[PDB]
Image: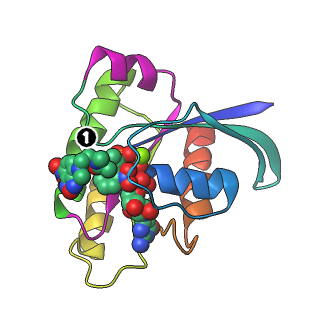
Amino acid sequence: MTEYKLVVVGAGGVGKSALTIQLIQNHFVDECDPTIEDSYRKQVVIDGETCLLDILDTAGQEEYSAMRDQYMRTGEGFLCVFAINNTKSFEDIHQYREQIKRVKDSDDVPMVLVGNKSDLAARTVESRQAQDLARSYGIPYIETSAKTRQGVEDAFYTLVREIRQH
Ligand SMILES: C[C@H](OP(=O)(O)OP(=O)(O)OP(=O)(O)OC[C@H]1O[C@@H](n2cnc3c(=O)[nH]c(N)nc32)[C@H](O)[C@@H]1O)c1ccccc1[N+](=O)[O-]
Ligand SMILES: *CC(=O)N(C)CCN(C)c1ccc([N+](=O)[O-])c2nonc12
Ligand SMILES: [Mg+2]
Protein backbone atom coordinates (compact mmCIF):
# COMPACT_ATOMS: atom_id res chain seq x y z
CA MET A 1 0.00 0.00 0.00
CA THR A 2 0.97 3.63 0.26
CA GLU A 3 0.75 3.99 3.96
CA TYR A 4 0.34 7.43 5.54
CA LYS A 5 1.78 7.66 9.04
CA LEU A 6 -0.18 10.24 11.04
CA VAL A 7 0.49 11.33 14.61
CA VAL A 8 -2.19 13.16 16.58
CA VAL A 9 -0.76 15.61 19.15
CA GLY A 10 -2.10 18.25 21.56
CA ALA A 11 -3.17 18.94 25.11
CA GLY A 12 -5.20 17.07 27.67
CA GLY A 13 -8.84 16.55 26.77
CA VAL A 14 -8.67 18.23 23.34
CA GLY A 15 -10.22 15.19 21.57
CA LYS A 16 -7.26 13.28 20.09
CA SER A 17 -8.37 9.84 21.18
CA ALA A 18 -11.97 10.66 20.25
CA LEU A 19 -11.16 12.12 16.77
CA THR A 20 -9.19 9.04 15.81
CA ILE A 21 -11.58 6.49 17.25
CA GLN A 22 -14.27 8.38 15.26
CA LEU A 23 -12.20 8.03 12.07
CA ILE A 24 -11.08 4.42 12.64
CA GLN A 25 -14.45 3.12 14.05
CA ASN A 26 -17.15 5.68 13.11
CA HIS A 27 -18.51 6.25 16.62
CA PHE A 28 -18.05 8.73 19.54
CA VAL A 29 -16.39 8.08 22.94
CA ASP A 30 -16.47 9.82 26.35
CA GLU A 31 -14.49 8.14 29.17
CA CYS A 32 -11.49 9.78 30.98
CA ASP A 33 -8.91 7.20 29.91
CA PRO A 34 -5.27 8.34 29.57
CA THR A 35 -4.28 4.98 28.08
CA ILE A 36 -3.10 5.12 24.46
CA GLU A 37 -4.02 2.13 22.23
CA ASP A 38 -1.52 0.70 19.76
CA SER A 39 -1.62 2.53 16.41
CA TYR A 40 -5.02 2.67 14.71
CA ARG A 41 -4.87 1.30 11.19
CA LYS A 42 -7.36 1.51 8.46
CA GLN A 43 -7.48 1.08 4.79
CA VAL A 44 -9.31 4.00 3.28
CA VAL A 45 -9.84 5.70 -0.06
CA ILE A 46 -8.71 9.33 -0.14
CA ASP A 47 -9.17 11.39 -3.31
CA GLY A 48 -9.53 8.06 -5.18
CA GLU A 49 -6.35 6.52 -3.77
CA THR A 50 -6.59 3.31 -1.72
CA CYS A 51 -4.16 3.60 1.18
CA LEU A 52 -3.40 2.50 4.72
CA LEU A 53 -3.57 5.06 7.46
CA ASP A 54 -1.62 4.31 10.57
CA ILE A 55 -2.56 6.76 13.28
CA LEU A 56 -0.63 7.15 16.52
CA ASP A 57 -2.91 8.62 19.17
CA THR A 58 -0.57 10.26 21.74
CA ALA A 59 -0.86 11.54 25.44
CA GLY A 60 -2.01 15.06 26.46
CA GLN A 61 -0.56 15.96 29.90
CA GLU A 62 2.87 14.59 29.12
CA GLU A 63 6.10 16.58 29.21
CA TYR A 64 8.59 16.10 26.38
CA SER A 65 10.77 13.03 26.87
CA ALA A 66 13.06 10.72 24.92
CA MET A 67 10.30 8.11 25.25
CA ARG A 68 7.75 10.40 23.63
CA ASP A 69 10.35 11.33 21.00
CA GLN A 70 10.86 7.54 20.41
CA TYR A 71 7.14 7.21 19.61
CA MET A 72 6.69 10.44 17.63
CA ARG A 73 9.75 10.26 15.38
CA THR A 74 8.22 7.60 13.10
CA GLY A 75 5.33 9.85 12.10
CA GLU A 76 5.18 11.42 8.64
CA GLY A 77 2.46 14.00 9.31
CA PHE A 78 1.05 15.58 12.45
CA LEU A 79 -2.44 16.61 13.42
CA CYS A 80 -2.01 19.47 16.03
CA VAL A 81 -5.20 19.59 17.99
CA PHE A 82 -6.67 22.05 20.45
CA ALA A 83 -10.22 22.41 21.86
CA ILE A 84 -12.05 25.62 20.89
CA ASN A 85 -13.31 25.90 24.49
CA ASN A 86 -9.79 25.55 25.97
CA THR A 87 -7.53 28.57 25.57
CA LYS A 88 -4.54 26.89 27.17
CA SER A 89 -4.77 24.09 24.56
CA PHE A 90 -4.71 26.59 21.68
CA GLU A 91 -1.66 28.43 23.10
CA ASP A 92 0.07 25.12 23.71
CA ILE A 93 -0.06 24.63 19.91
CA HIS A 94 3.16 26.66 19.59
CA GLN A 95 5.00 24.18 21.82
CA TYR A 96 3.55 21.20 20.07
CA ARG A 97 4.51 22.57 16.66
CA GLU A 98 8.03 23.47 17.81
CA GLN A 99 8.36 19.98 19.48
CA ILE A 100 7.35 18.24 16.25
CA LYS A 101 9.94 20.17 14.21
CA ARG A 102 12.73 19.37 16.67
CA VAL A 103 11.77 15.68 16.90
CA LYS A 104 11.68 15.37 13.09
CA ASP A 105 14.81 17.53 12.77
CA SER A 106 13.16 19.45 9.95
CA ASP A 107 11.96 22.95 9.03
CA ASP A 108 9.09 21.56 7.00
CA VAL A 109 6.82 18.92 8.43
CA PRO A 110 3.32 18.18 7.05
CA MET A 111 0.88 19.40 9.69
CA VAL A 112 -2.81 20.39 9.99
CA LEU A 113 -4.16 22.59 12.76
CA VAL A 114 -7.43 21.23 14.18
CA GLY A 115 -9.85 23.07 16.40
CA ASN A 116 -11.94 20.32 17.94
CA LYS A 117 -15.23 20.35 19.93
CA SER A 118 -16.94 22.58 17.39
CA ASP A 119 -20.35 21.35 18.54
CA LEU A 120 -19.94 23.16 21.90
CA ALA A 121 -21.31 26.69 22.29
CA ALA A 122 -19.54 29.63 23.88
CA ARG A 123 -16.18 28.95 22.30
CA THR A 124 -13.24 30.83 23.73
CA VAL A 125 -10.68 30.48 21.00
CA GLU A 126 -11.67 32.86 18.26
CA SER A 127 -11.96 31.09 14.91
CA ARG A 128 -10.27 33.97 13.04
CA GLN A 129 -7.27 33.81 15.33
CA ALA A 130 -6.75 30.05 14.66
CA GLN A 131 -6.89 30.77 10.95
CA ASP A 132 -4.29 33.52 11.44
CA LEU A 133 -2.20 31.08 13.53
CA ALA A 134 -2.44 28.36 10.87
CA ARG A 135 -1.71 30.95 8.16
CA SER A 136 1.43 32.25 9.90
CA TYR A 137 2.78 28.69 10.12
CA GLY A 138 1.71 27.85 6.52
CA ILE A 139 -0.60 24.95 7.40
CA PRO A 140 -4.26 24.07 6.86
CA TYR A 141 -6.82 24.67 9.56
CA ILE A 142 -9.78 22.36 9.97
CA GLU A 143 -12.56 22.70 12.55
CA THR A 144 -13.91 19.34 13.87
CA SER A 145 -16.27 17.54 16.17
CA ALA A 146 -15.51 14.01 17.21
CA LYS A 147 -19.15 14.03 18.41
CA THR A 148 -21.01 14.99 15.23
CA ARG A 149 -18.24 13.85 12.81
CA GLN A 150 -18.17 17.34 11.25
CA GLY A 151 -14.68 17.74 9.74
CA VAL A 152 -13.18 14.48 10.98
CA GLU A 153 -12.54 13.36 7.37
CA ASP A 154 -11.58 16.78 6.07
CA ALA A 155 -9.03 17.18 8.85
CA PHE A 156 -7.31 13.81 8.43
CA TYR A 157 -7.61 13.57 4.67
CA THR A 158 -6.12 17.06 4.32
CA LEU A 159 -3.20 15.82 6.43
CA VAL A 160 -2.63 13.02 3.87
CA ARG A 161 -2.74 15.64 1.09
CA GLU A 162 0.00 17.57 2.97
CA ILE A 163 2.16 14.44 3.14
CA ARG A 164 1.77 13.77 -0.61
CA GLN A 165 2.77 17.39 -1.34
CA HIS A 166 5.91 17.33 0.87
C1 LIG B 1 -6.42 11.80 30.29
C2 LIG B 1 -7.05 12.37 29.02
O1 LIG B 1 -6.04 13.01 28.25
P1 LIG B 1 -5.76 12.71 26.71
O2 LIG B 1 -5.82 11.24 26.40
O3 LIG B 1 -4.53 13.51 26.38
O4 LIG B 1 -7.05 13.42 26.08
P2 LIG B 1 -7.60 13.32 24.58
O5 LIG B 1 -6.97 14.46 23.86
O6 LIG B 1 -7.38 11.98 24.00
O7 LIG B 1 -9.16 13.59 24.84
P3 LIG B 1 -10.43 12.66 24.42
O8 LIG B 1 -10.49 12.47 22.93
O9 LIG B 1 -10.45 11.47 25.32
O10 LIG B 1 -11.60 13.71 24.77
C3 LIG B 1 -11.72 14.33 26.06
C4 LIG B 1 -13.18 14.40 26.48
O11 LIG B 1 -13.86 15.26 25.58
C5 LIG B 1 -14.85 14.52 24.86
N1 LIG B 1 -14.77 14.97 23.45
C6 LIG B 1 -13.78 14.68 22.55
N2 LIG B 1 -14.00 15.28 21.36
C7 LIG B 1 -15.15 15.96 21.53
C8 LIG B 1 -15.94 16.80 20.65
O12 LIG B 1 -15.59 17.04 19.47
N3 LIG B 1 -17.05 17.34 21.18
C9 LIG B 1 -17.47 17.13 22.44
N4 LIG B 1 -18.61 17.73 22.82
N5 LIG B 1 -16.78 16.37 23.32
C10 LIG B 1 -15.64 15.77 22.88
C11 LIG B 1 -14.52 13.05 25.07
O13 LIG B 1 -15.68 12.26 24.92
C12 LIG B 1 -13.89 13.06 26.46
O14 LIG B 1 -14.87 13.02 27.51
C13 LIG B 1 -8.09 13.36 29.34
C14 LIG B 1 -7.68 14.63 29.77
C15 LIG B 1 -8.61 15.62 30.08
C16 LIG B 1 -9.97 15.35 30.00
C17 LIG B 1 -10.43 14.10 29.58
C18 LIG B 1 -9.55 13.08 29.23
N6 LIG B 1 -10.06 11.82 28.85
O15 LIG B 1 -9.35 10.83 28.80
O16 LIG B 1 -11.26 11.69 28.61
C1 LIG C 1 -9.85 10.49 34.35
C2 LIG C 1 -8.81 11.24 35.16
O1 LIG C 1 -8.41 12.31 34.76
N1 LIG C 1 -8.34 10.71 36.31
C3 LIG C 1 -8.74 9.42 36.88
C4 LIG C 1 -7.31 11.41 37.06
C5 LIG C 1 -7.88 12.09 38.31
N2 LIG C 1 -8.69 13.28 37.99
C6 LIG C 1 -10.13 13.15 38.24
C7 LIG C 1 -8.14 14.46 37.53
C8 LIG C 1 -6.76 14.57 37.31
C9 LIG C 1 -6.18 15.74 36.84
C10 LIG C 1 -6.96 16.85 36.57
N3 LIG C 1 -6.33 18.02 36.08
O2 LIG C 1 -5.26 18.38 36.56
O3 LIG C 1 -6.83 18.66 35.17
C11 LIG C 1 -8.34 16.79 36.77
N4 LIG C 1 -9.27 17.76 36.58
O4 LIG C 1 -10.49 17.14 36.95
N5 LIG C 1 -10.27 15.80 37.37
C12 LIG C 1 -8.93 15.60 37.25
MG1 LIG D 1 -6.51 10.27 24.89
| Residue nearest the observer in this picture, 3 or 15 | 15
Residue 75 in the image, given as x and y percentages of width and height? 51, 28
Q: Is residue 130 left or right of residue 6?
A: left
* Image point (41%, 16%), residue name: 70
Q: Relative to 96, does residue 87 appear above or below in the rendering?
A: below
Is 59 rendered above or below residue 149? above
Residue positioned most to the bottom: 121
Q: Amino acid at mark 1?
A: Gln
In the image, is residue 150 above or below residue 44?
A: below
Q: Look at mark 1 in the image and give the residue it sits on.
A: 61
Q: Residue at x 68, y 61 (%)?
A: 26
| Residue positioned 30% across, 74% down in the render | 127
Assess whether residue 70 is covered by the magenta stretch.
Answer: yes
Q: Quadrant of the N terminus?
A: top right
- Horizontally, residue 148 falls left or right of residue 100, namely right
**Callout 1: SS:** loop
Q: Position of residue 60 (x, y in %)?
A: 31, 42
CA neighbours of label 1 inside 10 A, class few (<14), some (14 to 19), many (20+): few
Residue 154: % across, % down: 59, 63
Q: Nearer the viewer, residue 97 or 123?
A: 123
Q: Quadrant of residue 97?
A: top left
The stretch in magenta equals: 65-86
Label 1 CB less than 8 angstroms from ligand 1: yes
Residue 137 seen anywhere in this rendered image of the structure = no
Seen at 57% across and 30% down, the residue is 38
